[PDB]
Image (cartoon, rainbow, N blue to C red; front, top):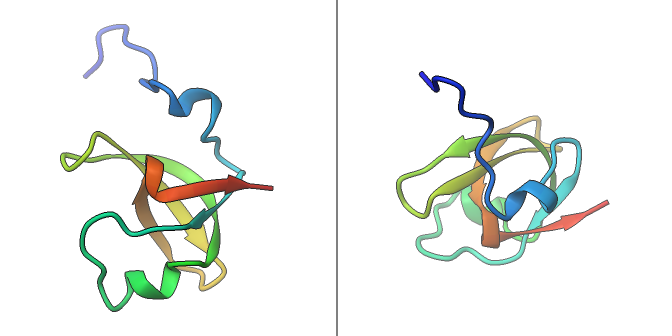
Amino acid sequence: MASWSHPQFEKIEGRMDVGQKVRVCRIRDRVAQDIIQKLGQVGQITGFKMTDGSGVGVIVTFDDRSSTWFFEDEVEVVG
């Protein structure tokens, strides 16, 4: 469902890109045992995700071969 709507990116359009690497700098709300591992760890954007917590989410695949989602402001873009 979209009718004619294009991929919706507000500010992340020219900041967050698939293939670019990102590092989790700060966990905004709650930190899980798994998430805390990724905190300070560098991963790569493999896609975007929709969230109901803060709008847009970013799917980051790390060197652990695991892919998890983080928020727009929750990560920094590197590489």
